[PDB]
Image 1 (cartoon, rainbow over the protein chains, first blue to last red):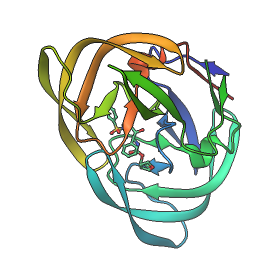
Image 2 (image 1 turned 180 degrees about the vertical axis):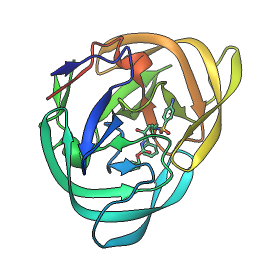
Image 3 (image 1 turned 180 degrees about the horizontal axis):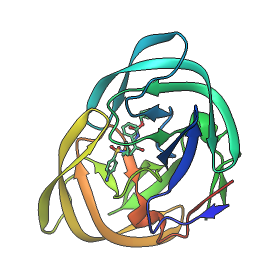
Length: 99
Length: 99
Ligand SMILES: CC(C)CN(C[C@@H](O)[C@H](Cc1ccccc1)NC(=O)O[C@H]1CO[C@H]2OCC[C@H]21)S(=O)(=O)c1ccc(N)cc1
C-alpha cells in the first residue's frame, strides 16, 4: 500500500498470535516494542533515542506480520513510548519513502 | 525520488542559508532540529521518545527547503542528536511510505 503522513502511520501487526498497533518509523534503525513476553533466549542490551538510553531485551529471529507482509528478525522489547517498526524490518517488507 | 531504507534516510535541507543533513522520519509528529539560534519568537515545549523527554523551542513559520522542495512551518529546536524532518513537513513535500 501507499500511506500518506497527515496521520501517524500506525498499522496492525501480528506477533505470536497477538494483534498490536505499531508505528512505521523510518527514523528508527531498530524495531522496539513495548513490554511483552516473547519465547526463547534473549540478551540484555541498551538503545538510545531522543531522550537518552533505555534498557531493552533483545530477542533474535522473531516473525512479525506487518500489513500482510512477513518479517523475521531481531526485536527489542523495553520502555518505548509506542511499538516502533524500524528500518531493520521495513527493509524486509519492501518499504520505501517516495515524494 | 524513491528513498531506500537500507541506510538512514538522510537528505540535505536548507534553513536560513544553513545547509544541514536531516532524517526523513515518519515516526516524528513534528520537525526538530539541532540547536541553532533562529530569529523571531518561540514557545517552549517538551517532546518525548525513547529515553524520555527533552526541552525544545517552537519557532513560528520558517521556510525550509528539503531536496529542493519548499516547505514552511513551525519548527522545534533543541538538543536532539540528529536533525529530524517530521510528518508536519513530509506532508508538505509529498512524501509517502510505500511497500
Ligand atoms: C520514538 C518515536 C515514536 C518518536 N521519535 C522519532 C524516532 O524516529 C527517533 C528519531 C531519532 C533518531 C536517532 C536518534 C534519536 C532520535 N527514533 C528512535 O528513537 O529510534 C531508536 C530505535 O532505533 C535506533 O536507531 C535510531 C535511534 C534508535 S523521537 O525522536 O522521540 C521524536 C518525538 C517527537 C518529535 N516531534 C520528533 C521526534
